Image 1 (tube, rainbow over the protein chains, first blue to last red):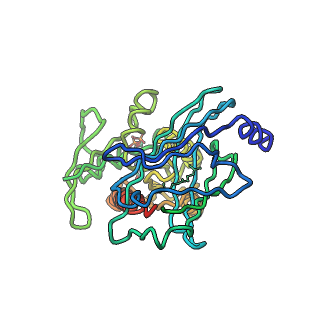
Image 2: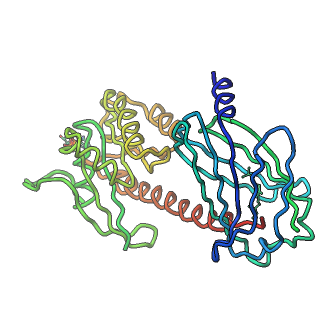
Image 3: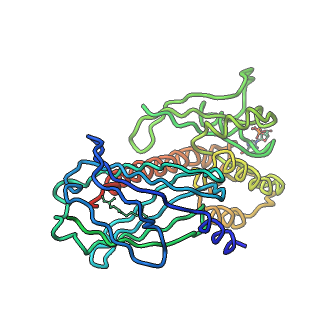
Amino acid sequence: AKDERAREILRGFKLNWMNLRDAETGKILWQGTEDLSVPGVEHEARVPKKILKCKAVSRELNFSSTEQMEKFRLEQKVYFKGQCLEEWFFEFGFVIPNSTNTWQSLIEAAPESQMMPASVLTGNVIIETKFFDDDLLVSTSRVRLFYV
Amino acid sequence: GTEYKLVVVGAGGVGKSALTIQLIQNHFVDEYDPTIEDSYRKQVVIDGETCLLDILDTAGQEEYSAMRDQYMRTGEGFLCVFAINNTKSFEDIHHYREQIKRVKDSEDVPMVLVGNKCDLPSRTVDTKQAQDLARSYGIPFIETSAKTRQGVDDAFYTLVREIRKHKEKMSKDGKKKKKKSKTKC
Ligand SMILES: Nc1nc2c(ncn2[C@@H]2O[C@H](COP(=O)(O)OP(=O)(O)O)[C@@H](O)[C@H]2O)c(=O)[nH]1
Ligand SMILES: *C/C=C(\C)CC/C=C(\C)CCC=C(C)C
């Protein structure tokens, strides 16, 4: 029953676009329209290295869902050379059936001392993203991150 | 100058009023006191820190739904009182705990279990039964006699220490989230 509901949600779920903006200035640094949320294939993303100098970035995800969800949410694990560097939890909440929604998250930079150079990070960062509706796992996907 | 709202709950006749009067006025029921008992503000020093205890005896208010809701929402810590000669009052304890937990929508509400009237020889609730219940909840158990004053301060002071542990834990978590919630991307 839970297996069937997770299948139904993923079948009706679509990631339309995503972008990253500098939080202070609002200028779009990167935009993707690929469904980087597809579970089977490891996706690649090439983001400008100036992203690392931003005091904070705003990430916007636009998605559609045929199925209603009560507590739509995300868990992200950031791996650097296979070691978990960071863990993030984001909550959207209630998704109206057949709706299309924009979800904005603010991600503030660590102090300058703890920031890692683009030359060290590039190609060695994997972002594993799990999409959930409460405690129900809908999908897992991975993106390999390059800084160019 | 921090105010701790302490709420004394338990079945009728267990000694909630007697315990409160003994904390506040340093004496057992004696002379006539026409005072309507609800809440009382008392300055005390616990472990070298001066604080204000806002102590609510719920004997009157427990019968009224909106009053119960209010004292369970506003209370920071709860004395859950039974009498050691009344097995029914001990059986009622879990009802009070579950109500408080539901109203506050939290699993670690500061509480102390109190077995009152320990001056009486006709005991029907063993110290071990009571200790087991308290261990099952992860809270202190203290035996009191409002009549002799045994354990009265200990009961209320232990509850304040439980509130302080809770408050100190919440402030460390708030700091720990601030530090953790920054990215290297
Ligand atoms: N022997 C004895 N009697 C007590 C003690 N505490 C309260 N009582 C008596 O038990 C009765 C009920 O006490 P009260 O404080 O009115 O209970 P409440 O209804 O829980 O507030 C009264 O007759 C009190 O004198 C105690 O520690 N020892
Ligand atoms: C500060 C750097 C960030 C937030 C890295 C950008 C992340 C991606 C591109 C991958 C995000 C993947 C999903 C939202 C499914």
